[PDB]
Image: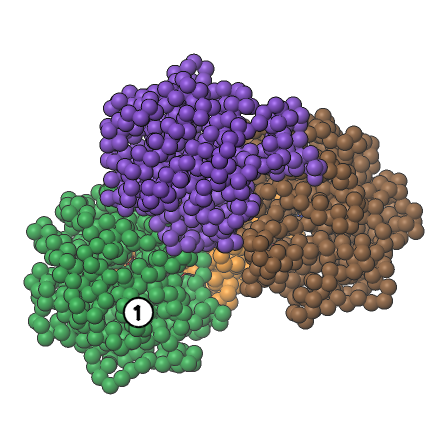
Chain colours: A purple, B brown, C orange, D green
Amino acid sequence: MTIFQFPQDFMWGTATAAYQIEGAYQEDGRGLSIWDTFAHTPGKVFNGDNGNVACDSYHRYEEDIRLMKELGIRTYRFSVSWPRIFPNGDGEVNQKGLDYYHRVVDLLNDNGIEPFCTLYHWDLPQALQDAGGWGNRRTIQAFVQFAETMFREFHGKIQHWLTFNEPWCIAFLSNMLGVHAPGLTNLQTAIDVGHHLLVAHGLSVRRFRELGTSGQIGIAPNVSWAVPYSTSEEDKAACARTISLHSDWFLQPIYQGSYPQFLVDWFAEQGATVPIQDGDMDIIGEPIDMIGINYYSMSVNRFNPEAGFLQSEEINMGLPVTDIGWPVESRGLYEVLHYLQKYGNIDIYITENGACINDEVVNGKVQDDRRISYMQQHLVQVHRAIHDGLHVKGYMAWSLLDNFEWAEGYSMRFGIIHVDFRTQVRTPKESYYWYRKVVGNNWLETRR
Amino acid sequence: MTIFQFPQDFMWGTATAAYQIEGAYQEDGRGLSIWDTFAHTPGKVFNGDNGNVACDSYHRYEEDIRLMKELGIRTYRFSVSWPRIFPNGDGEVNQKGLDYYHRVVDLLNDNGIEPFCTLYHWDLPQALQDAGGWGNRRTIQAFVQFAETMFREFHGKIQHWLTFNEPWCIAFLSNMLGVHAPGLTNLQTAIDVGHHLLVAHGLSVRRFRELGTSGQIGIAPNVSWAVPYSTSEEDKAACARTISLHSDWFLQPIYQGSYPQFLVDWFAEQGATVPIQDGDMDIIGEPIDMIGINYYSMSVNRFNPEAGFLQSEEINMGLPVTDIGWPVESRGLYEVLHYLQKYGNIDIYITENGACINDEVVNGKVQDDRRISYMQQHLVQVHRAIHDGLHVKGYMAWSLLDNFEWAEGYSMRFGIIHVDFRTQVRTPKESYYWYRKVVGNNWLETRR
Amino acid sequence: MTIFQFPQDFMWGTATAAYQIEGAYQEDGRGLSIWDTFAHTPGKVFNGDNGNVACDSYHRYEEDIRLMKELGIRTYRFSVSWPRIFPNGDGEVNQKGLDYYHRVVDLLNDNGIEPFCTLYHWDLPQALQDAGGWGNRRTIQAFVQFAETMFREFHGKIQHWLTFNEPWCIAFLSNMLGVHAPGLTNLQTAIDVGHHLLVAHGLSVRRFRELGTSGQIGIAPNVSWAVPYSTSEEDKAACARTISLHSDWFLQPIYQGSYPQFLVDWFAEQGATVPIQDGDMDIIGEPIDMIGINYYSMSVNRFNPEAGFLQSEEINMGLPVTDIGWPVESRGLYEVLHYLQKYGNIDIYITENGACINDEVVNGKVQDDRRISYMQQHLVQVHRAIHDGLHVKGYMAWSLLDNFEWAEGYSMRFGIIHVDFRTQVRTPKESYYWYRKVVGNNWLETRR
Amino acid sequence: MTIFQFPQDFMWGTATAAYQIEGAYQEDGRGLSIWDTFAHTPGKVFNGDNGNVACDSYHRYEEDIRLMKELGIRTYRFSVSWPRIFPNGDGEVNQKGLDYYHRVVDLLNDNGIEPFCTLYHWDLPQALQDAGGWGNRRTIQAFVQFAETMFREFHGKIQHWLTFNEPWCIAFLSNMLGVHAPGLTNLQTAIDVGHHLLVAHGLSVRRFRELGTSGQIGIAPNVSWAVPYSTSEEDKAACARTISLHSDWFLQPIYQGSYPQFLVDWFAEQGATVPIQDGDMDIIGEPIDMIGINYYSMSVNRFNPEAGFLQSEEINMGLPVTDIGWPVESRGLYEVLHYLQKYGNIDIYITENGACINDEVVNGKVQDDRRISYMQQHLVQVHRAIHDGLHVKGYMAWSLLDNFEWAEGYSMRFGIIHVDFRTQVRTPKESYYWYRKVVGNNWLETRR
Ligand SMILES: CCOCCOc1ccc(-c2cn(C[C@@H]3NC[C@@H](O)[C@H]3O)nn2)cc1
Ligand SMILES: CCOCCOc1ccc(-c2cn(C[C@@H]3NC[C@@H](O)[C@H]3O)nn2)cc1
Ligand SMILES: CCOCCOc1ccc(-c2cn(C[C@@H]3NC[C@@H](O)[C@H]3O)nn2)cc1
Ligand SMILES: CCOCCOc1ccc(-c2cn(C[C@@H]3NC[C@@H](O)[C@H]3O)nn2)cc1
C-alpha cells in the first residue's frame, strides 16, 4: 500500500555472536569464558542449556555463509571469542583461534560479504574473571592486547569494527541484576565494570589509529526508550533515568567527555561513585567513526520508589508481545534515532533488530508471519529517519540463526533461519525469503 | 501484570444507533430517512445491505435490555429515529414513534440503566432532503421542533442528551466524499450542512435550558488523530488539517465563537466559504455541559498535493489492523484527550470506542480475543488521562450488537454481542464476559 | 462487479408439486395416483423411495408458508393432487381434498403471497389409468370436470393458473422411455397421451373463459435447448428434433393450430400418427394469457442413428455438472427465450429453474454455494432477455423444499430449504438467505 | 463418457518464454531488456517480483527437457532472449547467448522434441527502448538483424518459427493501458509500435525466404472473443471492436493488405492514424505458412461510452473463474477458430492455452483437478473444429512450468509442473500425468 525506497549504498546485514552460535567450546585450545562457567552453574540458564555445541558454527560456517550469499546480504556482523585467541587473556596467543577467524573472514570476502567485527560480545576469559574481571583495571590492558592482535591480524580483511556490544548488559545486567555472566548484584562493581569498559574502548580505538588499521571503528550500545505514563516531573525523570543508563551513560563520556550528572547524583546517593583516574576521560573521548544501536522494544514507565535501583516501573499498556514477552512498538526506534542527534548527526547502524517468534518447521517451512510483521514496522521507522536526513547507514537483523539466547537458552528463537539443535539442520524461515526481497530490491512495500 | 482502578462514579456503557439496530423501517407510520433511500440505491452499500430488519431491536428491545442488565452496565447510549417521531419532519407528530421510545426508556430506568439519548444519528427524513436537507436552513427549524418534542416528552426519564453524532461524517463524509447518505461530493454543500448543523445544535441547547429539561446536554464529534511522517512543516500542517476538520471545525465555534482560520483560508482557496448569517456564532456558542468523543484509530500522514481535498496522505506503517483494515494505536486516544484541553478541562465521555473483529459463533460462543485486546489497550489510555486529572467521565463500547455498519452493511462486526441476521439470535461474545468483569469490578488488569 | 436491476412488478417465487411435498397419501379419502402405484413397484424409484410422507406438507403447510413470508417472495407455485379432489376422477368430489387447498391458499393470501396453481403435476388418479389413462379420451372429460371444480372453488382466491406441467415428461418420458409413471415404452401411446393432453388443456381454458374465472391461465412446458457439435445438416436436424419435441410439439398447436410437420414425418416413418379428430386443433388453439417455461440444462448433440427414437446423441463437453449430473450452461435459457419469440413476444414466466446440490446441514446451516452460483448465472440470463424487450414476467426457484425427485427419490436435493426426512426439520440453506436479498432488493450483484 | 480421437500427426506441446523461466539475467553478457527495467521499477509488478532467477531454466534446461521426454510431448515452444544475442540490439553479437540456445535446441532434437522458436516474446533490449523502442523505425532494422542471425545460426536445427507473440499485448497492453513493459499510455505510440511490429515481421519473413531457412514461419496473436449482452447494434459493434483489435488489426494487413477500416475510423476520431509509408503494406502482406493463436477466455460485452478507448464493457455473467479471475468458457475457442476462417482454412496451432490454478505441493503432489477440468473442455473444442475440417495442427499447454506471470509476478501459477522459487524443485502436477495420457494415447475421454 506504501512503497519505502532505501538509499543506494544502504548496508543490509544479518548479526551473530561467537558464544551463541560457534559451539566447539573445548576445540583447538579454546579456554573457558565467563559464559561457559555461568551456563555450567545450575539455575543460571533456563533448562540448563549452554553454548557447548550451540549451532556448531565453528564447523558449519561454510553452510551459514552460503545461506547469506543466497540472501544477497551486504554485511555480516559476527563476534570473536576472546578465549579462542587468548585462552587465559594472558598474552600467549592461540594460532588455531586466529586460523578459524581467517577461514570465516576469507570466505565472507570471497563471497563479497563485508565482515562487521564485534571484538567483545560478552565472552570474557574465566582466567581474567578469577582476578576480578572487568572490575580489575588489569583486564583493560588484557583487552587492548586482544584488540591489537585482531587489528594487526585482520588489517585489510575487515573494514568495520565494534569494540563492545551492549555495554549496559555487560555492566548493569551482568553485575547489578545478576541475570547475565558473571551474575553479580552490586551497584558499585557494575559502575566499575562500566568505567573500565570505556577505558578499554578508548585505548583500543587509540591503537587502531596508531596502527592505521583499515576501515572504521565504533561501539554498539543497546538503546532503551521509555515514555512517561504521566505528565508528572517524577514520571518524566524515571523515563530519563531508564533511557540514559543504556545510551547516555556510555555515549556522553565518548562524545562530551562527561557522565550524565543526574545519574552520577542518583548513584552517589546509593553510595556509588565512578572510579575515574587521571587521563581516563581523555582516553574515553577518543573520536569514533560510527555507533551501532541495538533496538528491540520501548516501554511506558511511571516513577515507583520500590521499582529497582532506577525507581522506574514499566507499565503493561496491554500491547501485543513477542514470544519472549517484549511489546512491539516500532516508533521507539524512530524516537531514539532523533534523541541520539544530541551527539550530532553521527553515522548510526542498526547492528541488532529482531523479534522472538518460536514458530518451528511444519510441512518443510517456518510460517513466522509475526517476524515479517515485526521487521516491516521497524524498517519503516529506519526509512522514516533516513528521510529526516539522519545518517542511518545500515540494518542488521538479529539473528541469522536461532542461537543460544543467553539465560533463556534455546527456548527463545530470534533467527531468520531455523536451526534444529538435534540435527544442526538449517531451514530458512518465511522471514528469510521476505527479507531476501527487502535487501535485493532495496525497497519495501508495507501491506497485509 | 498492571492494575488500573477507575473513579467511583465512572459511567460504564454500550452504544447503538436507531437505523443500525431498530429495523421495522415501515412499521407504525415510520417515514423514509436519507439512509433508507441510500441503502435502496444499488452500489451505495456493500452487498446491497439495508436497515429494513437490521437487529429487529424495534421488537427485540426487551431481550437487548436484559443482556445489558446482566452486563451490569450503568449507561445505555441509543439514538432516536427522527422519521419515527416526525415522518416528514413537517410538525405532524407520530404517537407510535414516541410510544416505542417510552417502552424502551421505561425498561432501561426500571433496570437501573441511565439512558444516554443521541437526537440525530444520521436518520434525516427524506421529506426534508427533497427540500435540500441540511443545506437548506429550513431543516434547522425542523430539527429544533424534533429536539423540543423529545425534551418535553422524556423530561425526568432521560438525564444525558447529545444533539448530534459525528458532525464530520454528517457534513464532509456524506456531502464531500459521497461515502455516506445522502452521498453528494461538493465542498460547498458539505460546509453549508456543517454550519447549519451547528446552528440547529445551538438552538436545541437553548430550548433545553428554556424548557429546564432534566440532566445535561452536549455534542459527540468523531475525533481523528494524525502524526507527521516527517519533522517537515508541510507534513505537520497536513496532520493539523486532518485533526482540525474532525474536532476543531465544530468545537472551536461552540467553545471560542470562531472557525479555525487556517481551514477557512484552505477552503476559501478552493472557492468555498461558510454561509454565516447575523447572530449565528452567538447561537453556536451556547454553553454545553460536556462532549462525547468517538475514537477508533490514529494515523501517520505525509503532505501530498493529489491526496484529496485536505492534501493529507495516510501512510501504512505496517501496523496490525482490525478486520475493517484500521490500525490499532491506543495512544491516539491519550494524545487527543490532551489536545482537546485547549477548550479547557471539559467533561469528556468516550461515547464510541471499538474494533471490527468478524469472529462468528463456534462451539456456542465467540472467541473475539482481538476485541478484548483492543478494548484493554484503549481503557488503559482512559485511566492514563483520568490520572493526568482530565475529566473523562465515562466509556461506551461501540457496539452492544453487531449492527448495520453503514456503507459496509453487515460485513463488519463491531458488536460485543453476536447477532445472527438469519435468526436474530443474540450470542454474547467473549468480549461481553470480559467487559462485564471490568465494569462490575470497576478496575482493569492487563495481561495476554 | 455488475448490477442487474429487475422491472418494478417482476414476480419472484418458489415452486413445489403436490406428490413431491404433500405426503398424507391415504389421509382424508385421497385415492391412489399413478405415482403411488409406480413408487410402490420395485425397481421404478431409486432406493424404493415414495411420496407416502415426503415433506409432510399436508400437515406442515403453516411452517412452509411462514418461511415463504420471511423470504419476502411474491408468488407461490404449487400443484393440486387430482386424487384428493376426485379420488377416482369419477365425479364424486372429496370435500376434505378442497378444505386442505382452501386452508393453504387462504394462508398464502393472508400473507400477501399470490398463489400460482398448477392443476396437473403428474398426479393422474389410478382409477382413470385402469381405463387406459391419458391414452383414453375418457380422461379428457375427467380432467375438465376437475379443472372446472377448482376454477369455481378458488375463484377470486387464485389469479394465476397452469393447466399442465412439462407435457413432454407426461407423454414421452412417461410412455416412450418408461422412466416416469405409468412407465410405458410405446411411441404411439406417448403421442396419444400428448394429443389428449392438449385437448384437455384447450377445453379447460374454454371453461375458464365461460366461467369468467379470476386471473390468467396458461401451460408450462419443460424446454430443452440443444446446439450442434458440427456445422453438418444432420447434427443441426438432431438438435431441431430434440428442441421441438419439448416445446414446439405442444406450443405450435396452441399458437399456430398445427404440429411441427418435420416431427410428424419423423414419427410417421416409425409407424406413429396423431389421433386427431374433428375440431381438436380448434380446441387446442384456444388463446392463453402466458406460458411457464421450466429450464435446467442445455446440451451439445451429434446425429447418431442408434441414439434413441430422436437419433440425437448428447456429447459430454467436459463441463462441470450438478450432483444429478446435468451440466450448467445458463446461456441456453437466453437462447430458448429468443427461440420462443417465433410465437411472438408472449408473456413468459420461469415456473421452474434450479440445481441439484446435495449439501446437508453442517454446523447449523447448508453451505450450498454451488446453488447460489447456479441461480446467479441464470438470473443474469433473465435480466439479459428482459433488457432485449422480451416479456419475462417472473422467476420461480425449483424448489422451496428438498422433495421427492420422482425416479431419483430423496437422493437429489433441489430445495432452497433443507428438509431432514428423518425429523421433517426445515433448515433454510445459504441459497434461501442469498435469494431473500435478491427478491427483497429486486436487483442482483454478480461476484464469487 | 465421450471419446475424442485426434489426427495421427497432431502436434502435442507445452510452451515457455525466455524472461518468464530463464533467470540468469546478468550471466554470459546478457543486456537488460525492457522487462528487467519494468520489474525493477517499484509498483510495476505485484510484490516487486522480477525475472532475475525465475525458474533458473538457463542452468536447469536439462531437467526441464527430461520432464518433457517423460511427458511424451512432440513440440516445445520456447522464446529467444533478444538481449542474450544482441545485448544492445546494436549488431555486436554475443556468442555465449547463441551457445545456450544451441545447447537447449540440440538436446530437444536428440530427445526427438521439435523446437518451436518464438523470436520476440517481449524482451526488447533497453538500449533500443532508450531510443524510442518499437515507436522508432530503427528497431525494425534491429529486429531483422536479430531474426536473420537466428535463421542463419539454427538453420536445419529448427523447423517451426514465430516472429512475434501476442502483438495486441506488445502494442496496446504495453503502450495504451500501461500494464506491461515499457508501461506507456498513449493511443498513438501503441498504434506506432503495432505498425512497426508488422513491418519488422514482414521483413523477417522476407529474409527467411531469401535465406531459404529450414521449415515454416508465422505470427502468434492472442485472440479475444466477445459476445453481445444485447441484440442491439451498439453492443454488437463493441464486441466487434474488442475482437478485431486482438486478431483482425494484425491479421487483416498480413492476409488482405489492409487495416480494419472501422477501427481506423474509430482511432482517427481519437486523433490517431497509422504511420504507413510506401511499401509498408507490401512488406506486411509477405505470405506466412501458419499462425499461432493464444486462447484463454471469452466474454459478454455491452456498449459503454466510459468503458476505455474501445467503449466495450465486459459483464460479469456470474460464471466460475480461474485463480487469476478469468471465466472459463471453452466454446470461445471453437467460435474464434470458425471466425478466423475469414482468412481461409489456414494452418492454426494453439500456441498457448491454460488456466491459472494456484494449487501447491501437498503430500508430495499437486491436486490441480481444476486445471485438468479446464484443459478437458478446451481440447474438446480443438477436436470439435478439426472435425469441422479446420486445419488445427497442434496444441501447446501454457505452461510447462509455473513461471514469472509478468505484472502478477509468481503469484499466478499456469504451469503443468510445479516450481518452488526457494529451492527450484520441479513437481509434475496431476495435470502433467493427465496430459501425459492425452498426448501418448492421442485420444481424450471426457468424464467426471
Ligand atoms: C527480572 C526481569 O528480567 C531482566 C532481564 O533483562 C534483560 C534485558 C534485555 C535482554 C536482552 C537480550 N537481547 C538479545 C541479545 N542482544 C545482544 C545479542 O547478543 C543478543 O543475543 N537484548 N536485550 C535480556 C534480559
Ligand atoms: C474509500 C475510502 O474513503 C474513506 C472512508 O470514509 C469513512 C470514514 C469513517 C467511517 C467511519 C465509520 N465509523 C463507525 C460508526 N461511527 C458512528 C457509529 O454509528 C458507528 O456505527 N466511523 N467512521 C467510515 C468511512
Ligand atoms: C436413463 C436416462 O434417461 C433420461 C432420463 O430422463 C429424464 C428427463 C428429465 C427429467 C427431469 C426431472 N426434472 C425435474 C422436475 N421437473 C418438473 C418438477 O416437478 C421437478 O420436480 N426435469 N426433467 C428426469 C429424467
Ligand atoms: C485493469 C484490468 O487489467 C488489464 C490487463 O489485461 C491483461 C490482459 C491479458 C493478459 C494476458 C496474460 N497472458 C499470459 C501470457 N500470455 C503470453 C505468455 O507469455 C503468457 O506468459 N495472456 N493474456 C494480461 C493482462
| The quadrant where residue B53 appears | top right
Residue type, mark 1 in image: Gln
Taking the view exactly as shown, the residue that stands out farthest to the top is A42
Q: Secondary structure at mark 1?
A: helix
Left or right: C195 in relation to D206 = right
In this picture, is C89 found above or below C292?
Answer: above
Left or right: B189 in relation to A380 = right
* Figure disc tally: 1
Q: Chain of mark 1?
A: D
Instruction: Tell me the residue at 88%/50% (across/down).
Output: B208
Instruction: Tell me the residue at 29%/23% (across/down).
Output: A30
| The quadrant where residue D346 appears | bottom left
Location of residue A266 in the rendering, given as x and y in whole percent from the top left corner: 63, 30
Taking the view exactly as shown, the residue that stands out farthest to the front is A278
Report ligand 4 position as a quadrant. bottom left
The residue lying toward the viewer, choosing from B122 and A106, is A106
Q: Which residue is mark 1?
A: D129
The residue lying toward the viewer, choosing from B10 and B115, is B10
Res. B166 in view:
yes
Taking the view exactly as shown, the residue that stands out farthest to the bottom is D278
Res. A24 in view:
no
In this picture, is D31 found above or below A9?
Answer: below
The residue lying toward the viewer, choosing from B194 and D293, is B194
Location of residue B104 in the rendering, given as x and y in whole percent from the top left corner: 78, 39
Location of residue D292 in the rendering, given as x and y in whole percent from the top left corner: 22, 64
Instruction: Tell me the residue at 53%/40% (across/down).
Output: A257
Location of residue C234 in the rendering, given as x and y in whole percent from the top left corner: 25, 61
The residue lying toward the viewer, choosing from C48 and C111, is C111
Instruction: Tell me the residue at 37%/28% (across/down).
Output: A142
Neighbour tally class for label 1: few under 14, some 14-19, many 20 plus, Cα within 10 Å = some
